[PDB]
Length: 382
Length: 113
Ligand SMILES: Nc1ncnc2c1ncn2[C@@H]1O[C@H](CO)[C@@H](O)[C@H]1O
Image (cartoon, rainbow over all chains, first blue to last red; front, side, top):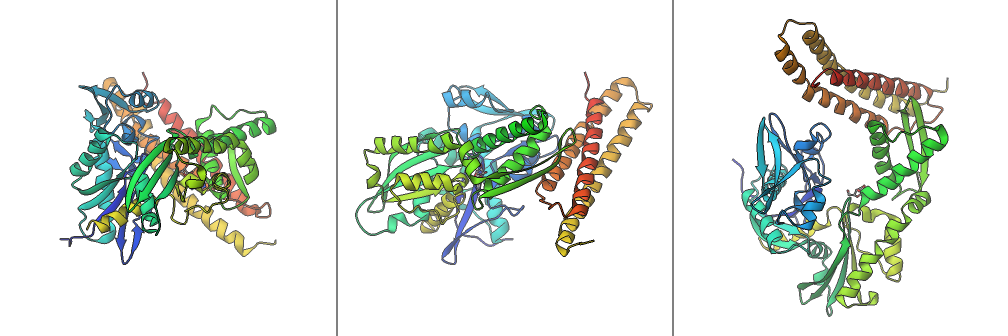
């Protein structure tokens, strides 16, 4: 059997999880069995098996009521928590009350089964551990696991418990903004206390955190954000733009044809990524609706206009976090970008102009920065 | 003609997608034969409903595989000069959509109440 391997860093995310390892003086972000550097935080229950990660996300359209995701939005919460009640109106899977605690309820191998959020997250963590072992060719037991800065005692404990159920020896639970600051070596910079703003914009979450680093100690000064603002909202604006354009060009409404909308949404998400490094993106979809070919393009300027209020709105939680931390924008020493949506040039421009032209910490892949810092912490604790 | 080496790259991508479509189409062909077999077969009625609803997982998997193919075809950008590629892309999308309509027919004949 396999030799004992190193300690790893795991960013256990809402929609995607990421695992890193510090080896040969650097962090290696580990690709999964499908070659992906992030793994969907998805668990599916079928008539014959349990699927985790990419294999679970890949069959979500075929088995929606038995494909669990967003377990992080439930972990460590009570059933009657405002967040649980609000989120369960949007999930296709059932959430039941078990003596005040939420449980996901699914059909598994023809039987009704219920699982606590930490059991679902333990399955995602088991997959992250296996991803590390498949790459290293060694057994992995030790890990640093990250959590949001706003997680209370119960949410932190439930995350630790998921790690324990997954067979991991959790070396430490550290905050996601702290892990991002660690990835950039912000604690190792010489001088007095450093005020750090972490700007975390993903596919479905926006979190601003202000930290003070003094003599290697991290203190969370404030947290602000928008729990459901992310990349998905920008894709929605692009889809609305193109549905309206098809109505103007062809006098046809494609919006009730689920497959035509999905084809358009997938092309939009891809065009949006193109717009972060090019000023224009082209889309060609043959026989989109009623045999009509849809050949179009969108400029970066048009994409920015469609989302202007949403991009501009990302500065409101920044001002709120600054107010709450009792700091002036001029007292921020470092700005860190986390989350794939921070790749948007207009978002970077607005944040840089707000901070009077100050350079942003963005060289580390924003989807990997948290796992990166966690893997640095894991090596230090080894 | 003015056939370019660059179009050969796009034609090769489309050929790979045609092969992938053929593999999914063979799975659909077996679903159609089993569906015809149940509709025109000698099973008793209660067993007929059950036998028909057992096709659900496979038909949904077939629909999803065809949708993934369409999304991959939708990543292609073919200049108007690449006429052969455009014709091949159009023919392939129409073939996948006709297969999706057959999948929808299977769905209309199973798990009914
Ligand atoms: N290059 C990019 N430009 C814009 N958004 C991106 C980019 N890469 C990833 N994202 C977005 O980040 C989110 C999390 O993966 C998704 O909404 C995704 O579309």
